Image (tube, grey):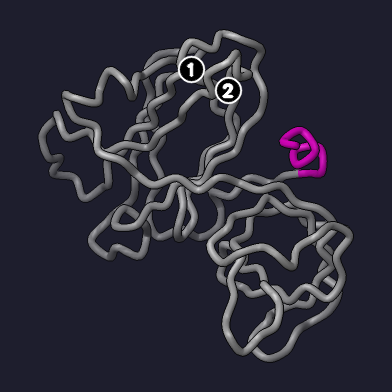
Amino acid sequence: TVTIAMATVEKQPQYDAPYLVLDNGEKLWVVQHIVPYRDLKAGERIFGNYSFLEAGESGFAYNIRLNDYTLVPVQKIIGLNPDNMDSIGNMKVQIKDMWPSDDYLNVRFMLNFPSPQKPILNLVVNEMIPWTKDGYAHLELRYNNNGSQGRLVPGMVSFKLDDYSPENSELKGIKVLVNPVDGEEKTYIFSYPLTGEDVPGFNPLDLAELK
């Protein structure tokens, strides 16, 4: 009866409230809210709890009740080179979910509680290895706990894909290298175009766990 899913806040001058855009591009108008939303800014990303109340109007696919959400940090891709390699790291990380959408690589993962340094997860272009011939984007996820060896807690992040996204028509897909906690370095492969089959199903506990 409720949908737990990602969304990006957007705004346009002619409207008097922020609205939500699902990753499939449908725009949702908020007609009821149980938590604050009016001060959300364009480009902010959320993992939210929606009730779809009825078909919308004026280009909004649906009018919704916003039951709850949590903010999801949005990170840029960075360049990995010999100078910053050491500070970027490649420590073992536990991935719970990873999937691309039109604009983002979405990752749910475990990170060490800050004790005190707050850990970093980056999505990098490796500038130290040759071009590949294969028509896929090649990126790497790099985790650094920055000394924090503490208890693991859940985390979500969205990396802006920009030129590595499915809107780049020259790309056959994306390959993402991960150094996993149980296992050896492995490649997640996602073909383009995205049909929606890559998107995991979530429930309220998934959202509750992230607050």
Q: At label 2, which amino acid type do we have?
A: Leu
Residue drawn at point x = 64 percent, y = 17 percent: 152
Whether residue 205 is in magenta: the answer is yes
How many other residues sit within 10 Å of disc 2, few (<14), some (14-19) or many (≥20)? many
User: So how many labels did they put on this image?
Assistant: 2
Instruction: Give SS at disc 1.
Output: loop
From the viewer's perspective, is 151 left or right of 158? right
Residue 84: horizontal and vertical position, in percent? 24, 26
Q: Which residue is mark 2?
A: 111
Based on the displayed image, in which of its 4 quarters is residue 163 positioned? bottom left
From the viewer's perspective, is 153 left or right of 10? right
Q: Is residue 157 above or below residue 7?
A: above
Q: Which mark is residue 145?
A: 1
Q: What is the CA distance from the residue labelled 2 to the residue labelled 1?
A: 7 Å
Residue drawn at point x = 46 percent, y = 60 percent: 102
Q: At label 1, which amino acid type do we have?
A: Asn
